[PDB]
Image (tube, coloured by chain):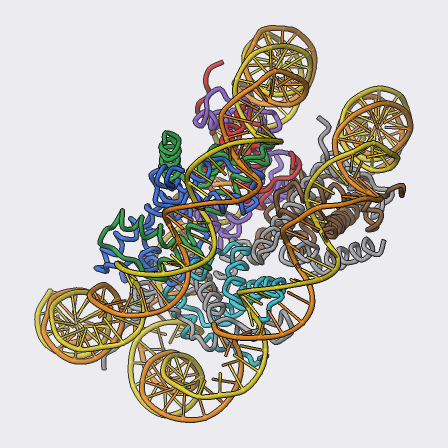
Chain colours: A purple, B green, C blue, D red, E brown, G cyan, I yellow, J orange
DNA sequence: TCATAATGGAGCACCAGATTCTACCAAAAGTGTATTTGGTAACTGCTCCATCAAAAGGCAGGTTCAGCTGAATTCAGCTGAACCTGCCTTTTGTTGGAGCAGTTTCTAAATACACTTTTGGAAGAACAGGCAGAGA
DNA sequence: TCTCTGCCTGTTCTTCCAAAAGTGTATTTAGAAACTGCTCCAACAAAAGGCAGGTTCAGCTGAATTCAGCTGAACCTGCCTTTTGATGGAGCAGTTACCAAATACACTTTTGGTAGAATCTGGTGCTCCATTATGA
């Protein structure tokens, strides 16, 4: 059976997902998460569908940017694998982390 | 009377919290900058809140929501408590 | 003519309700300004001022000084999580930094 | 319908991997998925808190796209394509 | 009685000078708005719009597409240094990211 | 009802830069957001400039200085050129 | 007056080292000083450009502390203690 | 003669300059720099003394914060020495490079 | 982990520069009218959001299985630190000269504020042209 | 990373209604001129403390190797999502009839700003510690 060497399919995936623009999280679980978070601030909240879509667009843009920073921090440490410490450093220098 | 500042009121508040403590002139300048900056933040957010909801008037609801949006966590709770208490006392008079 | 009573004294505040009302009216923040908006804003500004000054006077007491200086304001702001959040993009002139050496840098 | 709980785990590992691939990440630690879920939950909490504050000020019960747009813009994360 | 003509036509603009003047007056920016302020602002808005639209149409043509889409606006903005700087804190819905793989990740 | 937008003027500008290119409605929404965002930036900075210099009027000087403060480099240069050309054309009428 | 006399070198190596020490830095590469000079030159260029735009709008010839405070606030770097 | 080992005086200085608040760049050289790079408004600008002092306070605050971020990046790469690449990573995560 | 230097902290005395604390005074905040408009307060339509049900089909989850990357250990040279001179550049204290930033009349642009009048732009509907959906 | 279909959707024509245009007046605002006092700039000088350079040399950085951990890649399955289609009603937006409440205008009084003097707190020398750092 054919096997691609590690990182070949990863590079193909990088190209595929940087080429496209669609949302990479599933809409229904993200909506459930959004409603779950929101019920701590007010009960019996309703959401416009476009509100949930705005939240998902903003969240995915934020996470893609944070992953770009994380990959830079991983490369600075002479690694290719991103680790939680890379996310932590990117967040610290962004001012998101104390 | 040419300039105006919060020094008088900052010093009243200081004598309230710390009777025996003074304040430097540079510290008073920083406190003035702080009060002006926070006033600008809250007033601007209240202005935007009124514009969003198509209202002509900035009320204490706009100020309260601006405080909630701007201040973090427990600062917002205690600021809202103080503002509501102040408006209640003012209205009773 | 009843003798004048300041709106700050009516609200039980130290900060100026009338000046705050005039500054709201003069800042082009909106067409109109309610009667309780200056009172609320003065109360919030006084609360925040009292918070910072409490912490700064505590810092002044720690350093055995009887007078607050910009260093003490900086210490109070940066040692408080919420004030540091509020004033995270603010520079305090002559305030310095918090003493903090990364543990990796200390002698073995 | 029962009240929602534990919906962060619906941000699956493959979804996080896709978001990482769009970020140019070739290799991912196994511990990145829980870290990512925590970071996402904090971001969503911050944005939804402001969105609900805007919703409550307007005396509405529905959170609209403009409330989200205002909450994001308030945080320096301006979003185009949903109003404004 | 002259038959009236838009201030955009007088200024030689496509963007609405009258609407922009009304938005300036009603936006609570100042108590007065000058006559040439809306003309200047509408001209600047038209210039920036044309700049972005030219780059986005170039991107659309490169993609063999006859129509601009949020992806083309994203590509135009992020491939241009000035527009990227101006719109650096902005996320465009359904614009994606620029294709960019770090050189060290490519096959060794 | 009957909300306003810049769609008409953005399509008029597009027909100038690219006569044969169209634009999707989502792209036009992005462009409306862009125009309103930049209008708010310029207008807010011009309001601040008028306040700083203790003026009541926002004139084309305020818009010019706001454009210079807000746009970068060549964008600011070309935008100032365009606004000045527009105002010179408008006043000559 | 106007000066152009290579005085970015007036921001000396010991001064940059002191700034690094207040930043918690224990060991400094010898290439850090020219890097820091470039970074400071860029930062100062941005702030002074905004400050002089503010000065020119006011039709003044003198750059005042308020112009600098406004430029810094515009850059996202609010400063207390100079009349804000 | 007495010799302190490397890093001992460096740590003493870290404590010294984190304890203090005085400006760490000489005033006159910084004033010359400020007047020099005012190539904006060619020419003949005057400066208030407090204008240059506000500039210097902002500049030193900016550099101290940037050195804090640089030191975090250096530690993340398992180093004690800050290098130009650490400054570059800090400025890129901050959004200053682009 | 035993003694010697080097450093930073901590008592005292002596200022001297800054805070407090008073007095005047003028600018601005209360008082109190009229008065006008913005903003609740019902009272509906009407949209839109929220449950349900139910078929595909795609996606995610769990198992290998192996390759490759992260992590450690070692080693060596390099480079940065600590120190000591000798220099030089800043800092501070003076003049002085000049520019220029604020303060006051006065006037004349230019802006706001009202009508009616037309025009432009925002809803709708009708239609064909992109372009996503598949054919190797 | 390849032609032709068929649907979605962009473009484009009609209403009509909101708003932008032209007059016609009134009036603040801002520009212009003048004038003053407040910095700002610019030289001179003179201590002295930062700084620059050179020297050792100790520790850090980087390179090489090994190897175990881990994580990609592929493959089955299961599941869950997603896409219709109802429908129940929840709530949001629009239309009236007020009315509270904010604006606007004199007038008065008070309060906050600006000088001015006194004390007095913080800095600054000296000095005595008490830590730390550094090898036999």
Residue G35 picture location, percent across and down:
51, 68
Q: Does any portion of residue D44 appear in the rendered image?
A: no
**In the image, residue G68 above or below residue B45:** below
Residue C91 is left or right of residue I98, and the answer is left
Residue at (34%, 45%) from the top-left corner? C14
The x, y position of residue B71, in whole percent, is 43, 41
Placement of C4 over or under D67, stated as above or below: below
Closer-to-camera residue (J127/G62):
G62
Q: Residue at x 40, y 33 (%)?
A: B87
Going by the image, does I43 lie left or right of I120?
left
The x and y percentages for residue I122 are 76, 30
On screen, residue I90 versus residue G55, left or right, reads left
Left or right: where E66 falls relative to E88: right
Residue C79 showing in the rendered view: yes
Q: Nearer the viewer, residue J22 or D30?
A: J22
**Where is residue G59 shown, x and y percent of the image?**
63, 66
Q: For the point 56% across and 81% down, which residue is it?
A: G5
Foreground pick, E65 / D82: D82
């Amino acid at each position: 059976p054919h096997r691609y060497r590690p990182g070949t399919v990863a590079l193909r995936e990088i190209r595929r997902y940087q080429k496209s623009t669609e949302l990479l999280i599933r809409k229904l679980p993200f909506q459930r998460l959004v409603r779950e978070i929101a019920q701590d601030f007010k009960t019996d909240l309703r959401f416009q569908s476009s509100a949930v879509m705005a939240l998902q667009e903003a969240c995915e843009a934020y996470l893609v940017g944070l992953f770009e920073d994380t990959n830079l921090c991983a490369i600075h440490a002479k690694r290719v694998t991103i680790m939680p410490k890379d996310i932590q450093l990117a967040r610290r220098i962004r001012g998101e982390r104390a | 009377t040419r300039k105006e500042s919060y020094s008088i009121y900052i010093y009243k508040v200081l004598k309230q919290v710390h009777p025996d403590t003074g304040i430097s002139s540079k510290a008073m300048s920083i406190m003035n900058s702080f009060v002006t900056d926070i006033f600008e933040r809250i007033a601007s957010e209240a202005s935007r809140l009124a514009h969003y909801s198509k209202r002509s008037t900035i009320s204490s609801r706009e100020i309260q929501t601006a405080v909630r949006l701007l201040l973090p966590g427990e600062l917002a709770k205690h600021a809202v408590s103080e503002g509501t208490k102040a408006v209640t006392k003012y209205t009773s008079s | 003519r009843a003798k004048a009573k300041t709106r700050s004294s009516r609200a039980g505040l130290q900060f100026p309700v009338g000046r705050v009302h005039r500054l709201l009216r003069k800042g082009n923040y909106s067409e109109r300004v309610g009667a309780g908006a200056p009172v609320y804003l003065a109360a919030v500004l006084e609360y925040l001022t009292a918070e910072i000054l409490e912490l700064a006077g505590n810092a002044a007491r720690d350093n055995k000084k009887t007078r607050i200086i910009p260093r003490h304001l900086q210490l109070a702001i940066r040692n408080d999580e919420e004030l540091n959040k509020l004033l995270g993009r603010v520079t305090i002139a002559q305030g310095g930094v918090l003493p903090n050496i990364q543990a990796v840098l200390l002698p073995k | 319908r029962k009240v929602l709980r534990d919906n962060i785990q619906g941000i699956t590992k493959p979804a996080i991997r896709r978001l990482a691939r769009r970020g140019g990440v070739k290799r991912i630690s196994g511990l990145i998925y829980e870290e990512t879920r925590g970071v996402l939950k904090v971001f969503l909490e911050n944005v939804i808190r402001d969105a609900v504050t805007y919703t409550e000020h307007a005396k509405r019960k529905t959170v609209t796209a403009m409330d989200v747009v205002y909450a994001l813009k308030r945080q320096g994360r301006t979003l185009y394509g949903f109003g404004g």
